[PDB]
Length: 180
Length: 60
Image (cartoon, rainbow over all chains, first blue to last red; front, side, top):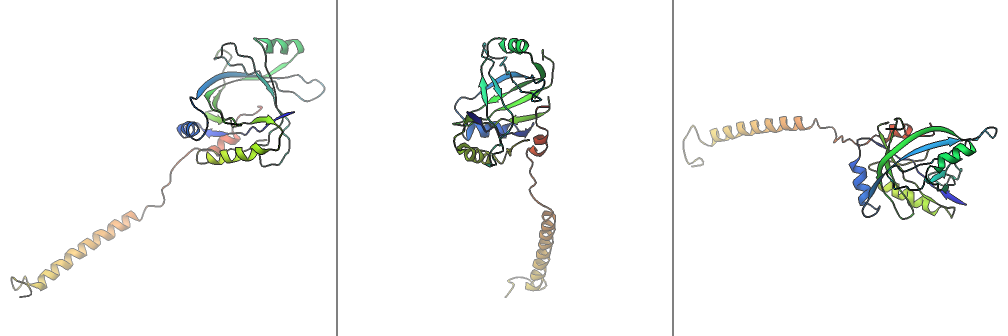
């Protein structure tokens, strides 16, 4: 039923102020904040030959927040000049229940990654800046990521033009686009 | 009088000295213009999203 319009964003590692101040100023929110979490992709597909990803992104800096998981894949060919995303389906989880259910039903951890950066929001949009590290479980590619994403029901792709205009607003700093 | 003072230092020598000073000033100005003409363009610098885009994270 629901859908998504997640757009990919990649800025140089040194260009940080021109992004943080512009996003804090143009139109995001009042009183911004940050975050920290690590993702755990999984896959359980024996004969179907379609590994379904289950990102159990748990916020390590959160006070027992649920392991909000999302399923994304199979980008729909809409050709609406949008972020070229697919339908999304969020799913909350309990404390250590994601790993528990992954072990019960049977899953294979494809990889593990951690993220850390600042947070931003919008009206019907959402942009996030963070940095990915490559380290063991106890604790980088030198490239930040602007996570301009939209998650909403199908509707009529009205938010696509708004997201395109918002990206054109931040054109002097970055240049968002789709991905394969 | 047409010079108000002197005979050898009259309007002739005054005009000669003024022309010499004007030639020196014009040479200085031409040198300054030739030195300033070297400016090609205000080449600023910004982020490089062209590489990090393909280098962005993925399922890999």
